[PDB]
Length: 138
Ligand code: NA
Ligand SMILES: [Zn+2]
Image (cartoon, rainbow, N blue to C red; front, side):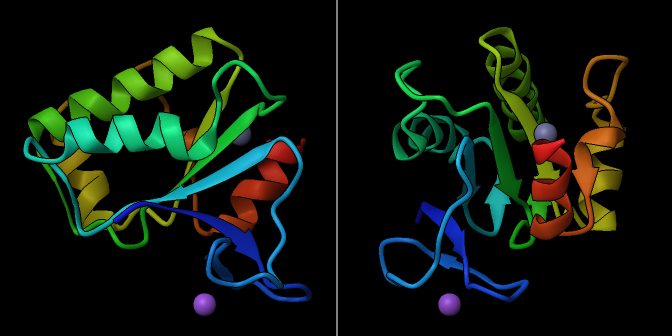
C-alpha cells in the first residue's frame, strides 16, 4: 500500500527500496508513493503512513518530501484538504513538499477544490520524480 522509492543507477526508474537493494535514495530526500486515490476513505492512512515510512520524526536531516502522484487517478474534497495540510505542516517544520507526475485531470480536480493558493502553488508540481529531485536538491 505505501512505499519509499529509490533510483536505479543510471536511470530515470524508481523502485521500492525494500524490494530492490540496487536502488539508492538521495540524502535528505524521501520519495513516498501511494495508490489510485487520495480521498476520504484513505486520507488518514496516507498521512499516517507518510509520517511513519519516511521517518521524518524530526529526528533525521530530511529536508524534502517528493510525493509520487503517477498512480493517483482520483482526488476528492477531503483528500485535497489532507494533502494541503500535509504540505503546510511539513513546511512549518522545515520540510519542502513537492509533487511528481500529477495528471491533468487530478490537477483539474484540485483546482476546483481551491487547493492552490499563494502558499500551495503549482510550482510544487513536476513532470517526473526526476525533475522533482533536481528541484529539491537546489
Ligand atoms: Na521496479
Ligand atoms: Zn522541493
